Image (cartoon, coloured by chain):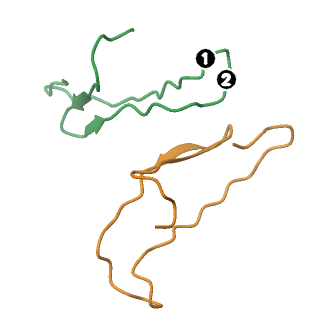
Chain colours: A orange, B green
Amino acid sequence: SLYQNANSYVFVGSSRYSRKFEPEIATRPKVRGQAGRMNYYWTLVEPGDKIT
Amino acid sequence: SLYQNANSYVFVGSSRYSRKFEPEIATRPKVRGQAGRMNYYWTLVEPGDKIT
């Protein structure tokens, strides 16, 4: 409904970070009205490097 | 091309270690010319135990 794609994937990349995510779908309890979860991430990009 | 098998699996085993790996395929940036990644591991084998 929101991404139009079947089973999606996400990749973020640098030199101090490298990981892939497979979204998990389940009946989680409601917190602020949304049963879904948002998981937040951060990374420091060293000077001259590129993030992707 | 290099392993002849569709979706491969690897298991390493001892008493202080137990894990299975599912190789992730993605378009990672090139470092030394190879877009692939090699992730290195180690474990100490206590005397008398067997690794697998």
How packed mark 1 is, by other alpha carbons closer than 10 Å (few <14, some 14-19, many 20 or more), is few
Q: How many marks?
A: 2
Is residue A46 left or right of B16 when viewed as pictured? right
**Identity, as a three-letter code, of the amino acid under mark 2:** Lys
Q: Residue A48: which quarter of the image?
A: top right
Residue type marked 1:
Gln
Q: Chain of mark 2?
A: B
Report the quarter where the C terminus of chain B lies: top left
Residue to which mark 1 is pinned? B34
Left/right of residue A26 with respect to residue B2 in the rendered view: left
Q: Which residue position is annotated with label 2? A: B30
Which chain letter goes with mark 1?
Answer: B
Residue B34 x %, y %? 60, 17
Asked whether B30 or A5 is in front, the reply is A5
Quarter placement of the N terminus of chain B: top left
Q: Quadrant of residue A46?
A: top right
Residue B51 falls in image quadrant: top left
Q: What's the residue at 26%, 28% (across, down)?
A: B9
Kindly indicate whether the residue at mark 1 contacts the one at mark 2 (C-beta within 8 angstroms): yes
Pick out the residue farthest to the right: A48
Q: CA distance from mark 2 to mark 1?
A: 5 Å
Residue A4 x, y percent position in the rendering: 48, 58
Instruction: Give me the residue at 67% from left, 16% from top.
Output: B32
Q: Using the rendered image of the protein, determine whether residue B17 is visible from the camera's viewpoint.
A: no
A6 vs A12, left or right, is left
Instruction: Tell me: residue A13, above or below residue A25.
Output: above
Instruction: Please state which of residues A1 and B14 is positioned toward the viewer in this rendering.
Output: A1
Question: In the picture shown, does residue B38 fall above or below A22?
Answer: above
